[PDB]
Image (cartoon, rainbow, N blue to C red; front, side):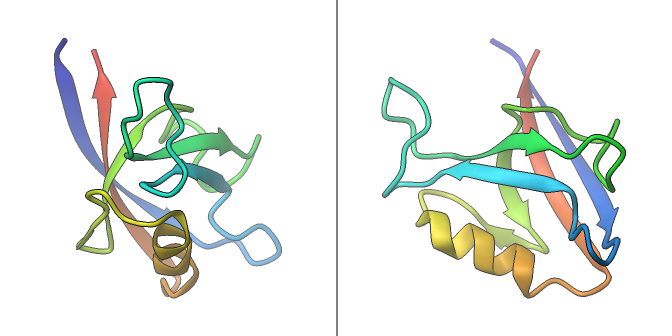
Length: 94
């Protein structure tokens, strides 16, 4: 494996949030391996993340806050408490 790490800034589109869904978390592992990583599970068509993130990107950080082995609701709450912008550091299996 290689992991490519990118950071993106998503601008809130009101009525549409940041146009992503997240899964995973240590209380909610997405993968059959039990890996606990927060992951992008859906990107809204036409929304703020279109062409910036894909399903299964691993989320390392949200607005500078580590998502290492955190609860699902902690990741959600970090997104929710973002301003106009959400800086999301991801890692992609390349």
